[PDB]
Image (spheres, coloured by chain):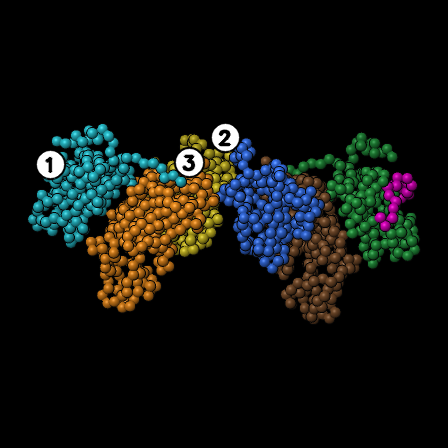
Chain colours: A blue, B brown, C green, D yellow, E orange, F cyan
């Protein structure tokens, strides 16, 4: 009756329903308000190697898609949650994301361009720059799927508990 | 020490320029990307960093009996990704809007050859309708301008046709456009995207239903800081 | 505000609209008409390697694609307009072409067979061998895209100005 | 007709009406809006050291003093506009001041807590966290004083032009 | 790494709490400062980092002919940094409001001996007035409270008299209050400020003219990051 | 969740209402009667360095001041209630005194001459030598202040529990 010894680098993907990521209904044109706030799990470390996909399935309250000319940005923040200026993993638009198969075809996938590393407390924020006319953002009818942990395509998100020298070098921020 | 970004219709600052050309067959500057004080430099590398362009023009018609067909739109049309069915494209060939009722209209059928279309909503007499179809013919390229107002020069002087931007599935990797040449910016310098064509591209028309912008231009680049 | 200089080797593409090519109307019972006349630029020089894509978007006046029993040939000539016979790059039918995606999928790209070179005067021509029925040919409602200078797929056409020894050996027809 | 040459380190003060600093009236209760912005003067370098005083005379359109419960924050940012969290210099209220003599008697002068440095483009922002009961924030009938270049009390801000080893050490940020 | 911040009536977030005491005399838990997830730890040091505390209360009256004077307000009406004239002080000893008129009021005369005051406008018979004088006598101190809702200890526990805060010019350096002892919060934990007095503290009375917070409690502190 | 550790020499000020003190209203011109009576706190020890201020808020029943010619005296006593003649710290008037900042401005802080150290059961008294016309002493409406601990000024007053042979020498206050 064995379990098999498993690497503590658990490969997963990430979404909104989890209890370390909070949403926020956004008005028209507040690009400084974070739609989503990813707080660390208070006990683990997350790693996102570069070359990593996103699926930000965004719609309005009526359910239609947002404007394609929208800008969508992922950014790491400080332990307070204010933007670092630098340290971006993504900056592009919604029109670049065909909602039907943005998570299906690797030939359509949009990937990261940078590595990233989140401790128990480090924070990520998803910002959205919108024109005035749009129908806001209804997180209750929209979601996000960061990474893949299911297919032989794409990549995943590594999560780990605390190991000694890994933590020793992780606190080299 | 550099990372990537996108320059676009709005982009990193509201100091860009967004204007429309002339009908006399003489090129103009559609867009102006001016650098801010924020960044030390901007760099674009053809064959590396993609570019996207969804151009779209503006036409108008008056209502009367039997006015379900729309005439030649003065535009050499093509399908999107080589596919015709409006409901199955990466983006519409064209959209239109009745003003008298103040709504969008769905399109029924197309004649790409005759550059004509067929609608469901037969309008009333004296009615007014506007159309925003993709732009057809057009020769585009890039240009540099210093902090003075002077043409330093173009880039890779072989203007690509407009319609190739329509022809391909721009979103799918490998098929996205990567133009040629290279170019570097500085703080008060302004690159321009220039175009020559018959027809008048447009933007920011309020009556358009599916966004505050009919038409877009985007470009992946690399940035110092 | 530098730009970055280039070598002479311009990697480009070719089509009807450029000012060194002329289309022509074609009836349906002549494989000997200059469908297209592609004349040199008078001072620059072109080169094409074998394995170069073609996209011959030929239709009729009513926009329909022509009978795929029709054959197409691209061929070199002399500086007057007399075909050299040899130096052919292509011979196939339109039935091997899919206008919906013929210039996008590599698995649909019909390519060249043998390389080619065009001096300041060398001519290329297109010839179209057609049966009696299929409604002739209109080039104003048709077009062509030769080579591809946008993707990593396919290849582009090389152009140069006059550089000495390169031209000395380019005279080695 | 002589004047006497100068050491590079000019001891000065700072105020609102200078051409490297900008004001902006704030609404009721927006903290993230920077009321006041300072940017490098494009060629010189500023050095503030700790124990630097403030006369932050913030008033409304009618000039009457604000709600003393208001919070003030002063912070260096990146070259883009994003605050750091790190590198805060000041955080205090209003009612801890007394506008009648907040700049007069040293028993009434609050000061900084850290040093600071501004390169040719570095940026500082000033934020104000406020309840709903404010009568706005009028910059015309308000002002600020930083530094002290008039008396033995307090300190002054040092300014220099670009000199070799000084700036070489300065760019270690 | 360390910085300096201020804990305040509203502080870095609205997990803070404030509430009142009883009419009989007992140490009640007035104001609680709870620590967020944003930070890592907090410190407060007496004799280094100062503290300001403006208490005030509420009484009220109904009007009648001859009611220019207001009686002993159930507290000892101290001076203000040893000063007597309201105009001359760092803050008022006393504020008044005619709610029937819906206006602020100003003071004519005072009598610290009999702890009484006398006003400008004799309000009408049946008129309604509210008054906010300073809190009188009483004692105040700190407390730690863990995540379990349980005490952990007090801090240099010599409960300070109330009047001393009113007796100094709290802003003036040297005269600024420094309490004593030390403390170190943790993440989900709380500190409390507690009080005993013969009168009822008040905040957020809507009818108050000067601001939304008649009374305040603010403190210079030291933070990690 | 620490609160930290403390010291012995706590630094305070002194006034009337503390519970080791007695106020007592006074007639016209009976100096022997004690107005204010400190006793020791029964277990701690008090120390008052020299150069140490006083802020006496002395008034009448009717809210006004007393005669400026009055003499305030602070005198050390036995453990019973008798004066001692020697061991006086202060003898001066009130016309030299000003109440509205007597604990704020050190330049207004009129101060002591001698040091002083008080043990468990010892007593200090205040006495008031007055003419006959005055209106006395209403201690409800008058008060006193002595030192300050929050500032860095004047000099705060020391209080301690017992530290050993320092106490053995302090107990040599005995005559």
Q: Which label sits in the foreground, 3 or 1?
A: 1
Horizontally, residue C31 falls left or right of residue F41, namely right
- Position of residue B136 measured from the top left corner of the image (x, y, whole percent): 73, 54
| Position of residue D168 in the picture relative to residue C119 (left or right) | left
Query: Which quadrant, please, contains the N terminus of chain E?
Result: top left
Does mark 1 fall on the same chain as mark 3? Answer: no
Q: Position of residue E151 (x, y in %)?
A: 37, 45
Q: List x then y, in percent, for residue C4.
A: 67, 37
Image position of B10 with respect to A10: above or below? below
Asked if residue F135 is positioned above or below residue B65 in the image, the reply reads above
Percent across and percent down for residue E212 are 38, 55
Residue placed under numbered mark 3 in the picture: D49
Quadrant hosting residue A6: top right
Label 2 and label 3: CA atoms lie apart by 16 Å
Q: Is residue C34 visible?
A: no
Callout 2: chain: D
Asked where in the image residue F81 lies, by quadrant, the reply is: top left
Residue bounds of the magenta highlight: C77-96
**SS for callout 3:** loop
Badge 2 or badge 3: first in the primary sequence = 3
Camera-side residue: D71 or F10? Answer: F10
Q: Nearer the viewer, residue B152 or C72?
A: C72
């Amino acid at each position: 009756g064995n379990i098999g010894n498993l690497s503590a680098e658990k490969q997963i993907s990430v979404y909104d329903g989890q209890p370390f990521v909070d949403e926020q209904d956004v008005p028209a044109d507040d690009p400084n308000t974070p739609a989503l706030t990813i707080e660390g799990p208070d006990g683990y470390v997350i790693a996102v190697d570069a070359g990593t996909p996103i699926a930000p399935e965004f719609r309005d309250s009526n359910g239609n898609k947002l404007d394609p000319s929208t800008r969508v940005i992922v950014q790491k923040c400080d332990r307070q949650g204010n933007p670092l200026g630098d340290g971006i993993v993504f900056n592009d638009t919604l029109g670049r994301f065909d909602y039907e198969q943005m998570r299906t075809d690797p030939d359509f996938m949009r990937k990261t361009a940078k590595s990233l590393m989140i401790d128990e407390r480090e924070i990520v924020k998803v910002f959205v720059d919108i024109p005035a006319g749009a129908n806001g953002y209804d997180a209750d009818k929209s979601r996000l799927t960061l990474g893949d942990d299911t297919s032989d395509f794409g990549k995943a998100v590594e999560i780990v508990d605390h190991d000694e020298l890994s933590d020793a070098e992780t606190r080299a921020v | 020490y550099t990372i990537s970004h996108t320059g676009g219709t709005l982009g990193s600052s509201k100091v860009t320029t967004a204007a429309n050309q002339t009908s006399p067959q003489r090129e103009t500057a559609i867009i102006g990307f001016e650098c801010p004080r924020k960044f030390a430099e901007i760099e674009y590398v053809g064959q590396r960093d993609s570019t996207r362009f969804i151009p779209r023009t503006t036409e108008s018609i008056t209502g009367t009996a039997g006015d379900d067909t729309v005439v030649s739109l003065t535009a050499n049309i093509q399908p999107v990704a080589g596919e015709t069915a409006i409901e199955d494209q990466d983006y519409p060939v064209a959209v239109a809007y009745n003003v008298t009722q103040g709504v969008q209209v769905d399109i029924d059928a197309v004649d790409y050859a005759a550059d004509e279309v067929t609608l469901a909503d037969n309008p009333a007499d004296g009615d007014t309708v506007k159309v925003w179809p993709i732009m057809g013919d057009g020769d585009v390229q890039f240009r540099l301008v210093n902090q003075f107002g002077q043409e330093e020069g173009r880039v890779y002087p072989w203007a690509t046709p407009l319609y190739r931007w329509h022809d391909f599935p721009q979103l799918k990797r490998g098929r996205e456009i990567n133009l040629h040449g290279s170019v570097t910016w500085e703080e008060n310098e302004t690159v321009e995207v220039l175009l020559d064509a018959p027809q008048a591209i447009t933007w920011e028309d309020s009556d358009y239903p599916e966004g505050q912008y009919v038409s877009t231009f985007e470009q992946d680049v690399e940035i110092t800081l």
